Image 1 (cartoon, rainbow over the protein chains, first blue to last red):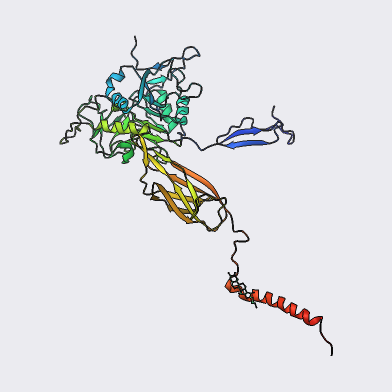
Image 2 (image 1 turned 30 degrees about the horizontal axis):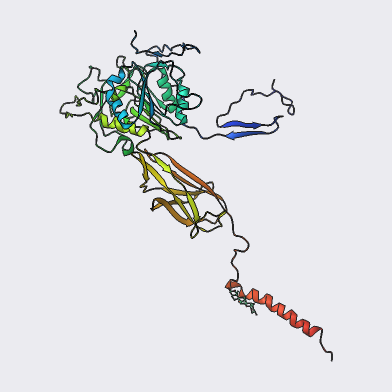
Length: 80
Length: 410
């Protein structure tokens, strides 16, 4: 699947993703590739998942959403 | 930002018990639409339009918003130019925590509260969960929290923390000196999250696109009972105050987030040589240059000229060669100076960044070319010999000719 016709050797890193670049143009035989340098990060994010302790069970909720049933869930909602 | 606003309610009766805030908000001139957080007809973009210019979340304890309100959708909404306000009580729910983690502010656990044992109001449930925050530990920027003096405020919410070396985040209201955030029922085993004066109560963000976001961390801060209560710490001898001073702070916060109090705008810039009126192409080296910019501030509903004591101009190539203070004349900040000896492509960066104001940034590119071959100094006095010499020999040659061809032998 991945093969370099010059360096007759299969590439080791099949999947690569960019963080500050994006592909702008790529010629027909992939001879010349032009990338676009994006704008700086809109806002900073946390490097880690927010704090989760083991004192109370997490009990993560399940998606429960189709392309037909688009209705969310609220814990503190008065039932009818 | 436009006046249309969306309110995400929790039980649809919350509007009744938050009536005062919304009546004020409408009186300022916003169009409020109240929906329930789980509503199938709920959406922000429709064919890339952003049909709601402001967003307000007063629905803590949500796990999935109704419709296509993801957390990536609200993130794209903040990246588009909108301004959100989110309030969260002691039942957080996952997507509010995740929105906080997207902006850079980390909420605490879902069952935690800002517990303080020295600053609890008399009107408490015996858990000391209600926390009376003083007006001392505030941000001290009059664009955000208003000009007047405020009475001690009331708070009942989850304590968040923000990165100390974070350039974008703000801290509108930190906790007290002894307040800690941990489960009120369970004993303290781990190190509690945000244990001291780094407990944040109200925390704001001013993004790179100038999108104002406020995390309030307590819904009851905006309530109708806390606008009209009476506050006094339960420590003996403490004074009793008639009004909680919560209303003025809430109004100032609401005005800041929805682009009404502190806004700056950059008008037309103009550079030209001293004595001319049109910008030349390719200034020469060491040429008098005049730079003029107009900055406007949104006062009430109209744009007025800006006061602006400290505003700096940078003339950069890769790193600044000249930095000067712009000076006000007429209605524009204008400065005249000289171009340095180095030739190249130089650009003017006027970047005004302040605590509370918007981020102003205007950079214009200009090329400083060296002297032409005609603009070199000529007929200098120091070289009057050499000139002489050359011409002397010319004269000599001519004389020589008249004496070399018509010479008479003897």
